[PDB]
Image (cartoon, rainbow over all chains, first blue to last red; front, side, top):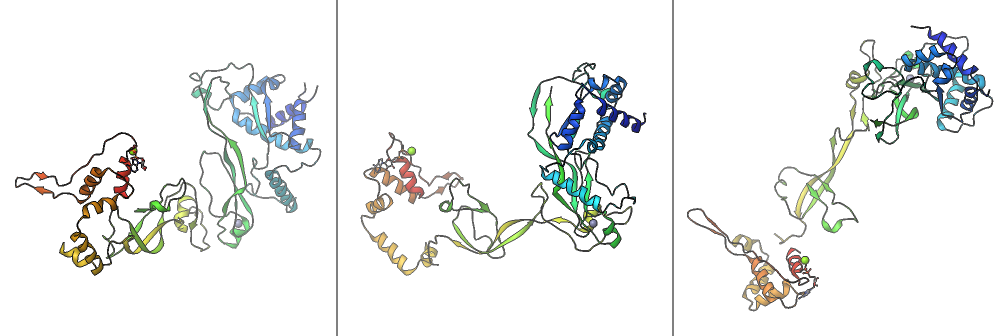
Length: 230
Length: 196
Ligand SMILES: Nc1ncnc2c1ncn2[C@@H]1O[C@H](COP(=O)(O)OP(=O)(O)O)[C@@H](O)[C@H]1O
Ligand SMILES: [Mg+2]
Ligand SMILES: [Zn+2]
């Protein structure tokens, strides 16, 4: 029970202010902004070098802080961005086009509903992960039990099996047959049900169907693998 | 259920098989093992749950939406719109069925079925003497020698008369033949001749 906005400002402080003097995370942020790097690896030893109690909070509550770190770095990218990305990937072209059209029709003073927004993971194009603290002792798969749920464990074992990289949905995208507005459905469950009707303002106002169709093209996927360690 | 004739196979291909529906009066005419020509439509019979991937689906074109608390989403939504996959499968609809290699253009019944030309042909065949060696030669023009095998296999094709006792013992009528010999002595060749 801590003020997550306060902790968000603190993780911003750590990301901006850390050095070793070369600003490790600053340079990684520049590389992120240029899209020369698709995943960032935070080092909890580096976190604890200044704020060990922050590392304590992360370890006792990891996934929350995965989300908070991701959001903070998303917010911090434009500060370090120097030059326009070269639009390497079709996904990057999609995010650039969506940013273009939302800035076009923004009406900057105007206020919009929370759901009339781009899902926060749809625009990232960077992953954030943790490298566990050396202070933590590597556990054993029998010992890791219910009291470790939601916590950042460190474990060692032999990888006995792994599936091949399959694409996994993270934000399904849909298009109406009426209003010409994309729709987005985030994903948290292993499975999901796909939408049918359109929640776009124009479709609801005109009281037309707007039976949106799922698009594999404008959606986001992430590489997905599963391994059985022991 | 019918499958591709052995002549029409492509290279490395399993014989495809498709299901043929036989409506009234053309119904018991086909039988298992025959070589039948079929004539009729190619229709499509609806299939459902043939694939684990979503495919083509029908739905009404009415522009209804869903009120709050009854919103046309999920299972309620699909039932309301009447969504249904359209997965089909070819199923031939045989209008008629004939043998692909008919025996006749149609003992007394078969004799009536005989045309005049074939009847006189088999008549002079029966009246022929040396029909023994003639049948040997006709069955096995390729073979040389092996006259005993020729004779035995011919008699096998004609067969004996099955009989049965008053008590109920089924006296055999068929006559089984065995060819045993050194390798490459036309044994499998004789069997192939009988097959073909
Ligand atoms: N007496 C024969 N007359 C004609 N062909 C023969 C004779 N003996 C052997 N052959 C030839 O030998 C080949 C193989 O004989 P086959 O019966 O297949 O051997 P196996 O009995 O081991 O299967 C045949 O294709 C056939 O042409
Ligand atoms: Mg053989
Ligand atoms: Zn719409």
